[PDB]
Length: 390
Ligand SMILES: CC#Cc1cncc(-c2cccc([C@@]3(C4CC4)NC(=N)N(C)C3=O)c2)c1
Image 1 (cartoon, rainbow, N blue to C red):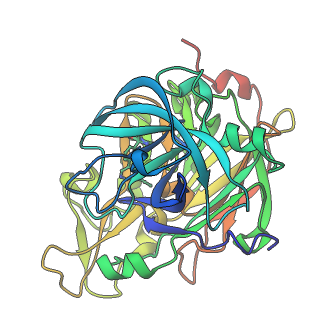
Image 2: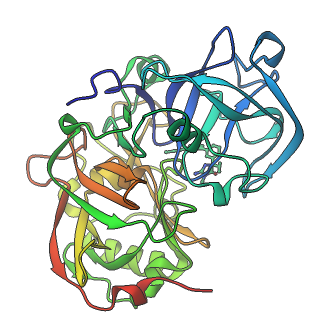
């Protein structure tokens, strides 16, 4: 590892998000910021909120610049309004540089901040195309690269603990690493395999084949990327398009048929519990996603275990049982490779070479019988036809 200063700079968990410490303004105001590859705005709480114990105070920053423009950002579940400005921004456990970046100062919000998440803002790491209000609002990473000598690349190691972390534990635990400008070899084992970034807006990729315990889901590959497939550190679940979700759940049910689970479990609503240490990992299948390779007609696969897709949760009765929720769910907006995928792998967002790399994570949870994997190459034809077009 050549980036010791950035290794282990993340905290949090899949259910509430992984965050990095940043500073905004002069003198520096410390805030915890959600690492989000699924959006492109740097937006921070800038007014009192019940779930915030701190926020950005523009009046206390001598370097604050008012852009005299508001922003209204409505999501599916949650929304926020803010005021656009610029200020000096740094990442203490990051590159040793300070940059002037756009900041959306959140003045009003609904279901945006998460009680107990320990973060006060979001760092949208995707491209300008999806920035709000429009693509003229330069994203943080674009500003960072343009103003410094930091290489146009970052890499994420999200570390699921494999068990529930209480309030105190989640604050004292290392949640992972965000390496700005490089690849740290201590965060992964084996080889890195790269898939092309199809288009620069979200981190869009193309899935060419899906298997459940080596059994091909056998769907037209276009279904897997309908209407897009993205890598999103800001989503908890592995989200699948409706038809893909229906086919995958049927196959996961069939593979795990020695034990029957209620519909609410498969719906990701209800947890399932087993006596301490008896989780029957072996009855649940592995899931492989084949991604388009960098070489013509070549693909590779990333394989996750139930230790990635079964999210550890504390039992309602805080008993000694090991409990989980099913962390694969349906989407009407394409595939979303969220923390379920990301926790299995070290993920390299190689913007300079328009590609995303995957390698087995040094912090993925597994058992003595199975491990997550990144393998290749495979001969795969007409992979371009797997990509969806409106
Ligand atoms: C892993 C993880 C996580 C996580 C947990 N709880 C809330 C959030 C959380 C909180 C606020 C906004 C967001 C968003 C919006 C677009 C900016 N980021 C994102 N990629 N997605 C799909 C969102 O809805 C996520 C993330």
